[PDB]
Image 1 (cartoon, helix red, strand yellow):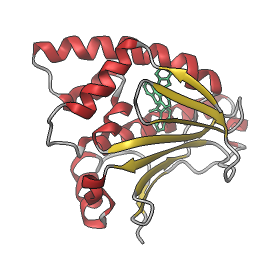
Image 2 (image 1 turned 30 degrees about the vertical axis):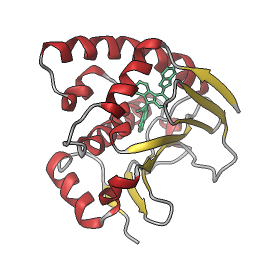
Image 3 (image 1 turned 60 degrees about the vertical axis):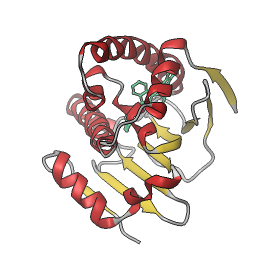
Length: 207
Ligand SMILES: O=C(N[C@@H]1c2ccccc2-c2c(-c3nc4ccncc4[nH]3)cccc21)c1ccnc2[nH]ccc12
C-alpha cells in the first residue's frame, strides 16, 4: 500500500465539504451515478471502433448496494474504469483545476449542489461518507483500490479482492448520522428525483 499527499487545493475542498453546514446532502448519489454513467458512455463509445474492448464484460450497468451491517453504500458500474496512472496522476490534475474553478464559483454565489459542473462531483461523497474506497479495473491495467478518509492523504494498492472484469466500485463508509441512505425507500426516492433518465439500467439491491 502506497500513501500520497493531496495537493493544497483539493485538500481544502475536502475540508469544506466535511465542515460546511449543508442539508441537501442527497445530491452525492446524483453525482456518483452521473460519473458512472459517463464512464459507461466512454467504454461503450470505444467499443464501437474496437469491439474487443468489451471482452472483459459486455453488460453495461449500474448497481446500488446498501449494507446496514457494514454501514456502507456501494455504487458499482461496468464502465471504463481507472488505471493506476489515472488514480495517482491524471485525476490529480483534474481535481486541482476543477477545485480551483469550483472554489471561485462559490465565492460568487454558486451552491455546493453545482459541484458536478466542475468535474469534481466525486468529492460530494464526503457529504455523507467519512471514508471512500474506490475499487477499479481498466482494460489497460490491473485491479486497484484507492482510499481516503481525508486528513490530507490517500492510498493506492493493487486489489486482491473479487475480480471485477472491468468497472468501478465506489464504497461509501457512511457517517453515523447518515444511515438514511441505506434505506430502500430513501434511495429509490433519490434516484427517481435526480437520475430517472440515466441511459443504463440502475438496479437498487435490497437486503
Ligand atoms: O469519479 C470517478 N473518479 C474519481 C475522480 C473524479 C474527479 C477528480 C478526481 C477523482 C478521483 C481520484 C483522485 N483524486 C485525486 C486528487 C489528487 N491526486 C490524485 C487523485 N485521485 C481517485 C479515485 C476516483 C476519482 C470515476 C472515474 C471513472 N469511473 C467512475 N465510476 C464511478 C466513479 C468514477
